[PDB]
Image (tube, rainbow, N blue to C red; front, side, top):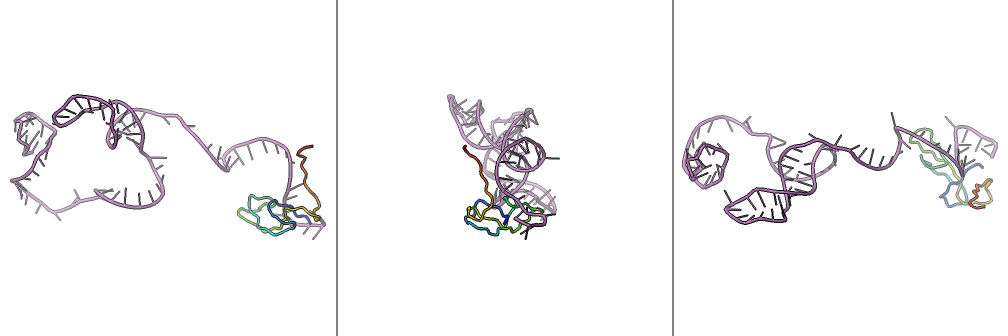
Length: 58
RNA sequence: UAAUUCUAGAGCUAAUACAUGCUUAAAAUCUCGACCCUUUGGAAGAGAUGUAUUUAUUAGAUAAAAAAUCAAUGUCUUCGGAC
């Protein structure tokens, strides 16, 4: 669908959260505002469409 | 990702952003008290004191005169201690 992954939620799905200032996946327009957005969980599965890979040793 | 002032991973470098942290007069006054050897003693040395926070306890005088008194003392000693 488009949604990104967030480390800390122990589900293989997506859910609605109330994001805050210094946390990733959100960027506030005014000061002191918080929005409810929807983010995808931290467990991989057949639904994904990309994946991040860092070569820690070749 | 069909999509909205949606955003993920990897790589750089700044501040009146964020996090730390030194400098300086002399004086006085307190407490502790090495010693001292003595009467009625005096003393080295030590530490404490900005402002702000919280609690407790004191100063923050005043309507009109003079003695007797208990001692202590500033002082001329008048070694009385009156002042």
